[PDB]
Amino acid sequence: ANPYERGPNPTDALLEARSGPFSVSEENVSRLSASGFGGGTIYYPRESNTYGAVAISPGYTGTEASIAWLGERIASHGFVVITIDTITTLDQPDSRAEQLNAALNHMINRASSTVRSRIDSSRLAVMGHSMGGGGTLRLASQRPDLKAAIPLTPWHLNKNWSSVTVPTLIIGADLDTIAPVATHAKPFYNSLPSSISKAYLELDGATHFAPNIPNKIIGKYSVAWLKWFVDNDTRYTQFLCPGPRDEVEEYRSTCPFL
Image (cartoon, rainbow, N blue to C red):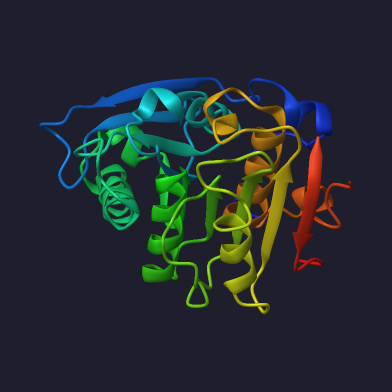
């Protein structure tokens, strides 16, 4: 038995639904309460258990409101998720890495007993949009004990992520003009080691802001990635490997993963 396994046997329909099967509550993190980040919202399963924990960063000028849907949706599949605000709207990717790190430490050590009691502090992941996705790659490089990293339409001036050993799913948007896949997402994917678990999923007919709107493909693949890498949930490998065919423009991976 896998002691980390949560929730029912998955299907495409259950993964593409707006909500998973776990009822969710929220805990506000004020700016005053937050050390090292701008505050945010913690989404957690009402059902008492331990779960993996995830921190998600927005991009430049963005706030937690732009990633709230994704925090709620992932939490509804059996994760504790914080959507952060940054200290300023100007903060760059390497700063968003530090703030993601501070948000994970907050959930583990400084949140209510309600939140702390629901976290397995040994099973952590990070995600983010645009510069938040650049932050995701930077923190993954600094914190190899993270179980997963999911950069969404990521932006970073550093193109070389050969130091990352955290299982990483990069989601690019084909029509992105702010973090074009040719200069950001693909170079990031290509520089990650060939020897790690990784994938690149490019959305078809998608702009840079696809991750800011509820999106069944982002929701399905983010949850499947977190289930396999954070929970060792073998029921989810079927969605990742071989993974989706040519609303997916392309899918590259180091499948098989199991």
